[PDB]
Amino acid sequence: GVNAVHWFRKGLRLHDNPALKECIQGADTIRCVYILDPWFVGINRWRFLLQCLEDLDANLRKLNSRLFVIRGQPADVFPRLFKEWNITKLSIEYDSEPFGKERDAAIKKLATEAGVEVIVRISHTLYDLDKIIELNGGQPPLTYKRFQTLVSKMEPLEMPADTITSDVIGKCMTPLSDDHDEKYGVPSLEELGFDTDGLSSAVWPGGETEALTRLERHLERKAWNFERPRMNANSLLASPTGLSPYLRFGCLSCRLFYFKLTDLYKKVKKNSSPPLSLYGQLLWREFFYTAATNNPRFDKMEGNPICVQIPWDKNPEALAKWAEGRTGFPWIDAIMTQLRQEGWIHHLARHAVACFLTRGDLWISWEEGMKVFEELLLDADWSINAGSWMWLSCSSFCYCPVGFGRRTDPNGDYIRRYLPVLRGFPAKYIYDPWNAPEGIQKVAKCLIGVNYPKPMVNHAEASRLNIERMKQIYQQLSRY
Ligand SMILES: COc1ccc(/C=N/NC(=O)CSc2nc3ccccc3n2C)c(OC)c1OC
Image 1 (cartoon, rainbow, N blue to C red):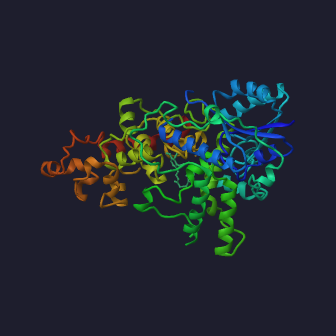
Image 2: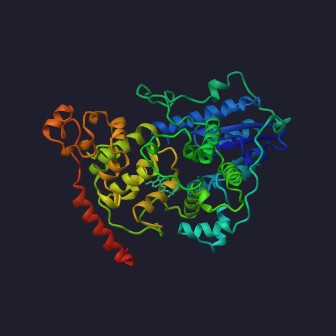
Image 3: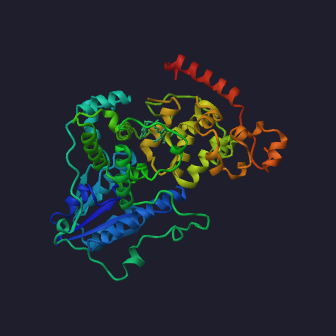
């Protein structure tokens, strides 16, 4: 009969999954596979992924199916699967990222050689990015405002695809052996080799089920403005309404999010012509995917045509201090600790630690900060992470590491939550503990230089030098 495989990579969901819906159409058997290579990334990313697969597996059970988790690399695994399962249809959600496109072109050639039809559908982005690039003339818009103009002229988005249900599955069945778990089951972090003794309950549980619950809560919060919210101290904490990791893994469809937001706006504001500001989260995301898709050096400075060639410092010791939250600036270190422990920090917290590392204090390449966020951050994939780091560092498209935190959370509770060694300090000194008298340091049981490091730069001197560097660079921008 007709034996189909849907290959999950992103799009880790059953709702709005047109590739999977089309693949099941006219198929006698369906197997959903995730190809896992744990030896080819921080532990919170692995955990989030595994939880996404457990959720997918549980939701597939409802359809008399299971997720097949296969170890290895797609180029080695799919030829054997095509033969051992007699596959003639393989579906994927389209991946616009350069190395994804290259991988998928290689797989499509194997599938062509084996007599397998490849179904590719766009549903990780709102638009066909290639059509945006055609509308701008063959080059991506390199400013957000130009991106918004292009997008506002595009044909309206079609409805998200129907969720896979039993009436959709129909006659299509999944052949299952009794030892499915032993051979195809979702592994634990331990079975990938990680110690989990230090881990607590995940602040960001993976999965489509979690995503659809959060989407509902997110919309209620927006219904009880549609303008960009203002950050306060509470905004720094992970929110039960946060959607960004779910959008990054495809647990939540960006198109379903778009339609629900539009429906809420129309119900609350009573106009069918909402401002594109309603969609800023999704359109910035779409902007960077568009910028990145045809630029295989998007995550690099040298050889990247859109990146200013800035002579960054090379300083592995300062880089590691920043990455490990040992800068001696409690605001910076608390943010980097939350990122390390939980996998998410507020975007203005991102601005602060990125400015500190790059154009503000340490003059280290944005490429280095990007790699750290890649390991630790749940919601930033290759295109978004690179684009955001170039944007922040003034490389394409000055935060005070004391006063920003002090203005955001003057009582210092954010610091005390993530930097316990500093809990004894009073508010007057919690953001600048080097300024506390030796008496206050001793009472706080935290000698600066012993129990918590001294600040790694003088901010005023470092920012003054770096602000002059960036002014001179842009005063001669064509040189760079
Ligand atoms: C240093 O790294 C980062 C720096 C900044 C941001 C985002 N800051 N967001 C704003 O300033 C308000 S608008 C907005 N919504 C977006 C959604 C996606 C991508 C960009 C976005 N922008 C600009 C970030 O998150 C992606 C980073 O992580 C990699």
